[PDB]
Image 1: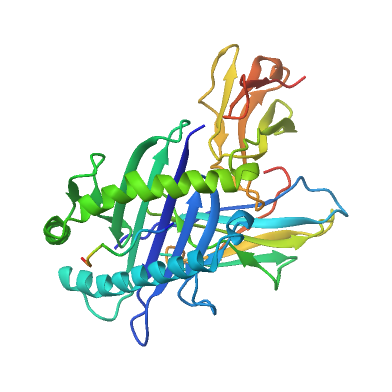
Image 2: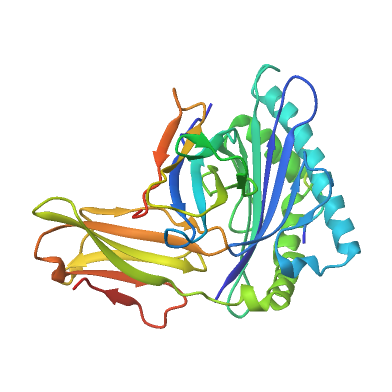
Length: 10
Length: 275
Length: 100
């Protein structure tokens, strides 16, 4: 089960 | 035994016409259960293990949705990173990302981690405290300050410590018959005559799961790290692994060499000799 | 940028017995970038139906792939894997030995 894209881009 | 759930993302830019290649694979210990390939027909997250095929459409719509959202974040990254490294638009570049959570035998959280890479080298990684970041280059430090502002570590910790370990425990009981089962190595030795006065003694460990195995050779009771050839553990292609350890022995003295096999599914380690 | 050459192992899934079907595997690992050509050969000729695992990598960021095909071994038939990557000047071919 994946997390969402809380990751901003670099 | 302990367990882990991990995701591996590989985005590779194809400068010239379209989009990057984005591969995403998910693993529970050494069993892969899902994948997404940017160039696959479906454009969905696919089952790669039987015990996940029985998941709901809603699961598959959620996971397809998240993984391609993740794809686009990486597409912006290859350009931004190229900017950070003042690179041309002619060369292909690769971004890799890996995150996951480890659970103990109690199924109570151990570690969480997230590491990111550019062109096969470290770029930025979450530290073992799930609070701070290791930035490699000065570019990686600009990313650190962005993620520091956007509070990525606080969100990511909640994932590693919450919904990762939860859904991991779930996978474990749902695919119990495979996942919670330790396949012990099927050992055996072979002997090839290298010459009239020397022989290779090769100790095998086959069809074992998990991949962790310590294959060790020794002579008269003491370790034989010398004249040992040890190959890296390889997949058999059915989900089990294989490995061998070989030692060059002077003829007539094979009796003093013992191979020692340690693996999670052996109550006591194996000691096998040639006679 | 980083370029590390593929480690290559050619072997069978199960112990190799003549007349019994098996799978010929070629495991390429430790390479970077992901662009690699891996072919399995029977007496020099390229086997047509060769499948492989989904791209995954190790902790030091190197990639690994497992290429496989069904094959029934014989004693007279010679099988091998041909791998090509930027790190190679000319393709690295390694022969399948039933004792490795």
